[PDB]
Image (cartoon, rainbow over all chains, first blue to last red; front, side, top):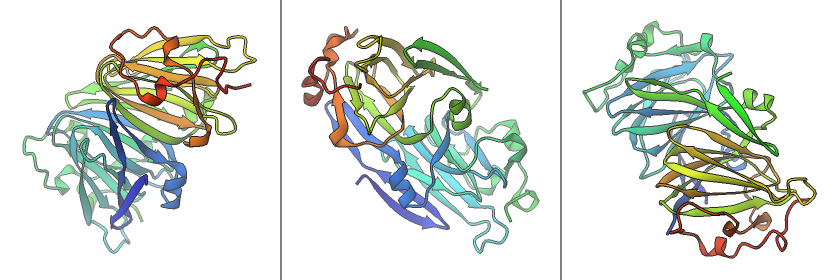
Length: 176
Length: 176
């Protein structure tokens, strides 16, 4: 009506858009500025997309202040295990995480505020859309924590050489 | 800037993003507010999605002032013929249209400013994302012109009852 929001912990929210099927296919509103603002999810200022073969893992990524990003993750085709880990030193849940299956069949989305490291595994070949808030892409602010922080369900992982080099949490430049 | 912009006339712009493929699949930046602002495409306030079976036509839609909408159309899966018709009564190209194929291979986008009627036919089963500017969804301001103006490639058209009723250019409430 047209969105159910569910707090999953730590400021992360599962968003569940309403899907309207008819003879043509279906339609949904994915995000709207007023409704999201009512939930204190600010406006999207950039959107990216990836296509990822089954077993791919991307992450775990974040940009540091002053270019911190919020993210709404959505999966129009396929299915992922999506993850957000608290990477804020002084948080009482620093290092805790939430996993959320996002897929084409649920159309659910994950909102991940600034201060979290994001990644996922592709459980099937998947298109992921990333609606990004706060700040745009800025290379010298990119950081990451190692994929190995998480025990991914598909063992036949496909990870870039770059992400394979991400540091452990204890050695990463994280949030205050 | 990782976009190329081709003017198709009347204010319509085809946008061609840079895609980065690798062993995982691919990645692209789809929209970036500071880059789009430079081409005078304002920021997104709502994003929708549809799935449309082969042969579907949706359109030709707009919202009237003062709930007018700009739209960037993108096709992450499939293939559409996208159409924008100038419905500004005082414009020198009143009633002229552009047609552009937008698809999952090219990853092209069409920027359709306020004052145009938008529609497409799905050439195969297709997911369309609509990035909407200026104003959110407003039912009392929704208007349309007949899809029957367009010689669609697939004769086996699948079309909603509502879109069947869309009026002629002469009888419709259009833009000044």
